[PDB]
Length: 14
Length: 268
Ligand SMILES: Nc1ncnc2c1ncn2[C@@H]1O[C@H](COP(=O)(O)OP(=O)(O)O)[C@@H](O)[C@H]1O
Ligand SMILES: [Mg+2]
Ligand SMILES: [Mg+2]
Image (tube, rainbow over all chains, first blue to last red; front, side, top):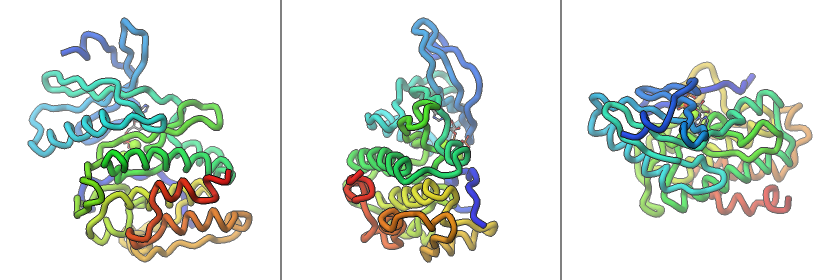
């Protein structure tokens, strides 16, 4: 099931 | 220069690649601010352009629902971007705490967010990193004003001229055109608004997978749905605005201006 979690930004492809 | 003389650092609010954000007090004024402290010892020409761009973009934007830059101070080995302190914490925390917003509270929230994004776009600024973690609350009293923050990934665009400006943003909020590595501009912000509004109404995101490749597949395909029970009571006009924001093709995606005139926002 989908959850609301904190997520870091990217500056290039990972 | 003049940060060491006038200002006093206190606790960390967050940390980045070669930067930290700390509460500071301009001593003689008795006024507190949030200071972004970038370490400038051996930065690339690129890294200098990005710092000057963030400073320039932040100086450009004067709006009730955008965090204001107070000052930009260049010292030996350290740069200080000094912003009005927002004390009510991240929109993210509030959603988790309340679980979700009522359509009235959600509408008032996304209205202020869209008025901020509209101003950005009119000034030729694309944020690229809209999400609940980058929206701050003016106070802890429910119904406080929201403020768009953190323009570290923001770009300058020349009118409606758009292009491939590189891969930047936050996985769950990334637009399909950025993941396809196609030309993009202002519409990537309205896709993020779509993700934020979905989160506001039922308290979880429209795109989630433990496997990032699969998350990106879902996003590129616009493979979201409105499951029971939390969508059972939601109005179709709320689902309509989300649908017009979560439109795969940026040409036909609703603009900030257009969204502000949607019955769900305006007749309200
Ligand atoms: N003007 C401000 N007032 C108060 N807190 C701020 C302000 N600007 C940014 N912040 C906070 O500082 C942090 C900025 O860090 P960010 O680049 O978003 O990465 P991370 O949140 O992972 O540390 C966040 O916690 C944000 O809420
Ligand atoms: Mg981040
Ligand atoms: Mg942030």
